[PDB]
Amino acid sequence: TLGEKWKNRLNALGKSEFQIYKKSGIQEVDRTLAKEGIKRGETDHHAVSRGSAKLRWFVERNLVTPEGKVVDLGCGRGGWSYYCGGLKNVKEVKGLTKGGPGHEEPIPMSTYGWNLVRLQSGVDVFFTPPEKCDTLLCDIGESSPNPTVEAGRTLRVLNLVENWLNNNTQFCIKVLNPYMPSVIEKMEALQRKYGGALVRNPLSRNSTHEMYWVSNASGNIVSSVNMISRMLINRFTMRHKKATYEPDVDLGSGTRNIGIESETPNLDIIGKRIEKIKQEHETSWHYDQDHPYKTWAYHGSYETKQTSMVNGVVRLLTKPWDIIPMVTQMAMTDTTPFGQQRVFKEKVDTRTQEPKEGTKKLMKITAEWLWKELGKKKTPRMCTREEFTRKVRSWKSAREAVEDSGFWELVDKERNLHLEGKCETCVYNMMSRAIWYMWLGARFLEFEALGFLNEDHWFSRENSLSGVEGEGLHKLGYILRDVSKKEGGAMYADDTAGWDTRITLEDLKNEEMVTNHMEGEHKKLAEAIFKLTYQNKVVRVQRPTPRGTVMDIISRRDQRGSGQVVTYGLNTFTNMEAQLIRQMEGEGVFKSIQHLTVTEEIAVKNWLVRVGRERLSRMAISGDDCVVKPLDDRFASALTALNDMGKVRKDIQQWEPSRGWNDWTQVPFCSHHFHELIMKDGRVLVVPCRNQDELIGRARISQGAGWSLRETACLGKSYAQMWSLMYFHRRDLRLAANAICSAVPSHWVPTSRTTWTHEWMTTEDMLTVWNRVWIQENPWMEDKTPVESWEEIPYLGKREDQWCGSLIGLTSRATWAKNIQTAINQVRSLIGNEEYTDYMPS
Ligand SMILES: Nc1ncnc2c1ncn2[C@@H]1O[C@H](CSCC[C@H](N)C(=O)O)[C@@H](O)[C@H]1O
Ligand SMILES: Nc1ncnc2c1ncn2[C@@H]1O[C@H](CSCC[C@H](N)C(=O)O)[C@@H](O)[C@H]1O
Ligand SMILES: [Zn+2]
């Protein structure tokens, strides 16, 4: 007896205990999304099974390094071989599985690398001749209540991978039951010849003793097996049987081509930049060899120390949300060791097929037209350092350094160099999302060149027709409605999968055309920004090595990296361009992306001049977020130009017609939907609204360290005064907002920062600010009669409120409301003895 002591404890165990025990303290991956998307026909990004994740756990620790020809016996739907398709050093993948009634048939998928992946069904790998291969995977092994049975099957598959192994071969072989001495004897033999060791995957459920014979591992067999046997036993009795959740594998998209992938850098530009990082180390520096990067250019690494609080005031006043998981889990921070590297390899380590010649012309003329149209009633310019320092409204405190005078001599050095045509301190530092931090000095230069776009309001709706820059949420809704009035098809709000990684080099050269309309000292500077630091970036990213974390530095030309405040401009620009070119395609201006006939290149030019402005007004565009009401619904199939520019829509098959909204109130825009609210006096309001959990959860989270109690309480007061001015139409949030203000000293000025208009920051009475923004100043309201009690401002309907997230009618919330006064005093008592107003209605 051994781990068989485990198996009878398990076989002798009820149905529900079994399911409880199965997923206890194990690691799981959220498959709800992929499983729903694969039914809807989405044939890329998604993994086809839990298997991809499982295998990724081995690969990212180098326990298997798949490479070359990859045979995959018992490939099932394809989880392992698809995953292997996108891996760097892999050149071919063949998957063989039985298939047939009772077994899994493979799933076809446009997953990254799929072109190198041949899955065959109707194949008994026990009956087929071996083939040359450089890495061999196998995942066969039927479990059974009976341990002797499984050793049988386990030994069968062990006797099979041996025919396929050579001695240099890489492998990952499931050992269904490694605790029987039948298997413990053969595995020792096998380990003597071919090496490796058994390794347990934490994503395996507790109901199977699977261990994987993986090539690049080492260790003693019997002990490794017994370690797992007691770990699985311990877990029968485990208190706290919740399961930890990983996000699933993002398996990419599109085909793989040895020639086309891989950056050829122009080290005559990124150069003076890298060897500077080198010198700042040169000791710990080393050119790693197993670097993961496959679409970026590697250069070297160096040591680096590996690298959100709850707001008690808000939290104490939102007690019914202490058990909603979509609220309390936003405060948790998911610091897996490979978690950053995973987002990089799946989402940023991607390439985009260069557009066709005809796409490129369409873009170049539309951009050429647009930049001119944007600059009719506007003129570029540099932006002062004093102008820059002025944003002392949010060394080691960009403020403190904004005057260390030294600073401006350092910014002064490289700035001449940009004028000569080089940089040295213009590197990005990377940190589901990525943010490309940059040196506080470098962000000056780019502000001094391109600051004018975000500072003279070039994408203001009034100046660029499609923009919504500088429009509060109390206007975007009326603006969408204004578009719905336009006569045409349905409203389309397609999102792009990972927009910034989809910026092409052509995209960047097109946007650089704003330097046409510049000239002088200025132009040369805004030429360096574009050419030197936008089209030719160098980046630092951390990465975990078996020698401890290192900071690789890599470089890539493609994609959008820049100041999150400057990229907004260009993203709107190019998206405006892209949505125009799509509108064309639907209307029929041009008919092929490969060539633009001279007589079509004219139609494009005409249309642009004859209706271009009108087409722009059919669009609400904020960066990659867009809303389009075109002439007819032929827009919903005009996908050739969209796809070829790289702006691949998110969450449907590449050539699936887009779905249009026939009710603007459901059109998602700027992370909100907008309801149409009618007062008791019958004036109509268009109000912003979103899942109320993302609102509560946001408000209960604090930025940074050192928040005192007076700050923590003024941050909550910001969130509350914002709720009552924007989300006043939701019961919970207006109650919670009133509670917060009754519990924070009424004389304290809210100061902090909510999101990214901010009328809720005044210390005025909120009802006054309400009347200003919603009545005496929105244009969509001609009757300027003031409302003089909160009992005049309306709510959504009950059913809408609880649909958009409310808790009204749940007993816990009802209890929260009867006692809100007890809660306000808990917090007031905590704050101390100050002057409090009482906003709660009776
Ligand atoms: N004799 C045989 N020949 C080929 N495939 C077999 C087989 N016996 C079982 N299999 C198949 O092997 C698969 C292993 S489970 C496959 C999961 C896979 N690793 C993934 O990532 O998706 C099962 O679908 C089973 O049908
Ligand atoms: N953060 C961590 N904490 C504890 N163990 C870790 C770890 N990260 C990795 N490991 C373990 O360290 C191992 C590195 S695998 C090393 C394989 C090696 N390249 C060879 O050729 O033999 C993984 O198996 C994992 O089990
Ligand atoms: Zn709503």
Image: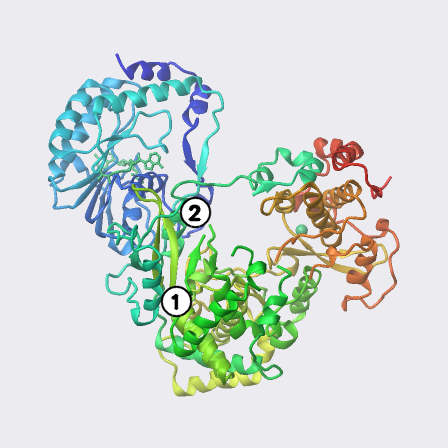
10 Å crowding of disc 1: few (<14), some (14-19), many (20+): some
10 Å crowding of disc 2: few (<14), some (14-19), many (20+): few
Residue located 46% across and 50% down the image: 432
Seen in the picture, residue 755 relative to 81 is either above or below; the reply is below
- Tell me the quarter of the picture where residue 673 sits: bottom right
Seen in the picture, residue 321 relative to 381 is either above or below; the reply is above
* Residue 634 in view in this figure: no
Q: In which quadrant will I find the C terminus?
A: top right
Residue located 70% across and 39% down the image: 313
Seen in the picture, residue 271 relative to 546 is either above or below; the reply is below
**Coordinates of residue 481 in the picture (x, y in percent):** 68, 65
Pointer 2 residue: 39
Q: Does the CB distance between marks 2 and 1 fall below 8 Å?
A: no
Q: In which quadrant will I find the N terminus?
A: top left
Pointer 1 residue: 424
State the separation of the CA atoms marked 2 and 1: 50 Å
Question: Counting residues from the N terminus, which is met first, the one under dot 2 or under dot 1?
Answer: 2
Amino acid found under the numbered disc labelled 2: Lys
Q: Nearer the viewer, residue 126 or 238?
A: 238
Q: Nearer the viewer, residue 587 or 349?
A: 349
Q: Nearer the viewer, residue 654 or 725?
A: 725
Residue located 27% across and 38% down the image: 100
Which quarter of the frame holds ligand 1? top left
